[PDB]
Length: 225
Ligand SMILES: Cc1ncc(C(=O)Nc2cn3ccnc3c(CN3CCN(C(=O)C4CCCC4)[C@@H](C)C3)c2C)cn1
Ligand SMILES: Cc1ncc(C(=O)Nc2cn3ccnc3c(CN3CCN(C(=O)C4CCCC4)[C@@H](C)C3)c2C)cn1
Image 1: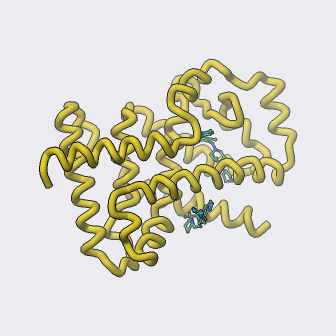
Image 2: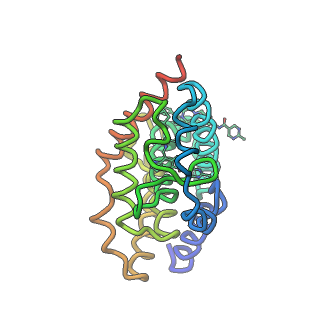
């Protein structure tokens, strides 16, 4: 691939990410000073587990839909056979959701954006998922310490999805090519911005897949209730 082809790939991925976010980063940052009061927190804690599930499931359904749209915008994805598109989405969509969550996490006071304001872990008490939510908060905290730029998170999340190592792929070589092109773009971009330091700091994939597995396990328990 030519330099121009690589540069265009970077810009396409980054635009695709920006245009498939639920809220713009500038909006999330502006709202950091908007923190649920003690009375509002108490109000959330009083809600039924079922209502809190509905509220979280509503948000997650939208987040997953946006990740699906992001995937469809990645060069070559829609040219893959249906099977391989599905394999990549099954393994990767919720991983991208978990990574994207860090945009809405404020490390200064350990709060997250939810339904208009920022609140801590205690907002979600009615769910009875303290261990899991703590793990999700910890993951976002570790990600926030990397200080991902908008372009970095776009390219990283593209690579979460486009991974030729996923079991069950029918056209492995085709996915290998897309993955390689994206990696070239990512490495090129990091070199240009002097940000290659982030690579060794990226979350261990075993950690991301195990957290995703635990998350999806709990989501499926709720769905069956
Ligand atoms: C034009 C157009 N028409 C329809 C869609 C669409 O239907 N979009 C979805 C949104 N969603 C929102 C929430 N769920 C969905 C699903 C189901 N998917 C179940 C498996 N998924 C997993 O994450 C588990 C699989 C096992 C591990 C986790 C995800 C990939 C989600 C689809 C298909 C999109 N565009
Ligand atoms: C417009 C808009 N854009 C982005 C966000 C966003 O990303 N916000 C969060 C970021 N985080 C970063 C780390 N943790 C978070 C949380 C905590 N959430 C607890 C409940 N959640 C469950 O999945 C339970 C359902 C039953 C099992 C756990 C998840 C939704 C995660 C939120 C809300 C919100 N709004």
